[PDB]
Image (tube, rainbow, N blue to C red):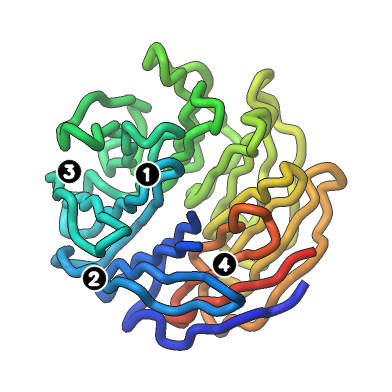
Amino acid sequence: YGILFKQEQAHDDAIWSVAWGETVVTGSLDDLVKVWKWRDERLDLQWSLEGHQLGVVSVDISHTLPIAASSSLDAHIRLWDLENGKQIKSIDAGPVDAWTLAFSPDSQYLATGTHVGKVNIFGVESGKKEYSLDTRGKFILSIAYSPDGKYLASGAIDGIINIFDIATGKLLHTLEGHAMPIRSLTFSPDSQLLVTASDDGYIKIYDVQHANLAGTLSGHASWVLNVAFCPDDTHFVSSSSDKSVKVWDVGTRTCVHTFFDHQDQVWGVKYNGNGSKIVSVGDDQEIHIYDCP
């Protein structure tokens, strides 16, 4: 493991979210969505996407199509054409009704968490709200689709996690788990495990089928801001307010590596397509790319 490339001043304010598709997409409070090309060991900026009127909260990239989606504090979601750097369309989510974004496995739907306790599912082609999942709870700070397309999970500001059945729209389970905010959750590539991160500094691992807690990892000294899975289905990576990025072994439930070369909160981490690179972004406005064996 090791630091491979650093882009200083990637953005002009905090970068809260990043997605890896060759192509890295970053969302920042400076209002911009930037598209970066990872090629021959280098990162180089391709597009600077203007349109949002206020800071960007979340971004995602479609798995099948060359598009990215951003949500912003300006109450809009924008879809972006990655091939030519232009905006496809802009959707009025509503005031604080658009926090974190995620494309569905097939990129026909885009889900967003709301301040009112709902997960709003938007249609990529139609631009309209196609349906809503209701937790009946509190500010939803994280959402995740299970790769297999069977489930959606949402983590709330008061520590409640909800697992929905995406084909019936019914709430299948509601977990107490944490009592602090859950700013990130992610399903594993085989859709069997659900890993959740929390302000309490603990990462919790749930089996999805039985819905029970499998383990808890200590290792972050402050808020866990992000968790993301390695394609090889065994590793995941976490980032935190404590300025560190950690790589974990799902099987042994232990830390394999920590990177400390960030000087502020690290908000975003993802593995690339073959799990040989990790990208990290945060408050220090830098993009780091790490090499993995």
What quarter of the picture does the N terminus occupy? bottom right
Q: CA distance from mark 1 to mark 2?
A: 24 Å
- In contact (CB < 8 Å): disc 3 and disc 1: no
For residue 254, what is the image quadrant? bottom right
Q: Secondary structure at mark 1?
A: loop
Up-down: is 9 above or below 117? below
Local crowd size for mark 4, using a 10 Å CA cut-off: few (<14), some (14–19), many (≥20): many
Q: Amino acid at mark 1?
A: Leu
Q: Sequence-wise, which precedes: disc 3 or disc 1?
A: 1
User: What x and y, as percent, mark residue 87?
Assistant: 18, 57
Label of residue 31 in the image: 2
Label of residue 93 in the image: 3
- Residue at 53% of width from left, 20% of height from top? 173
Q: Sequence-wise, which precedes: disc 1 or disc 2?
A: 2
User: What x and y, as percent, mark residue 137?
Assistant: 36, 32
Q: Amino acid at mark 3?
A: Ala
The residue lying toward the viewer, choosing from 119 and 110, is 110
- Residue at 32% of width from left, 38% of height from top? 110
The residue lying toward the viewer, choosing from 253 and 198, is 253
In the rendered image, which residue does mark 1 sit on?
65
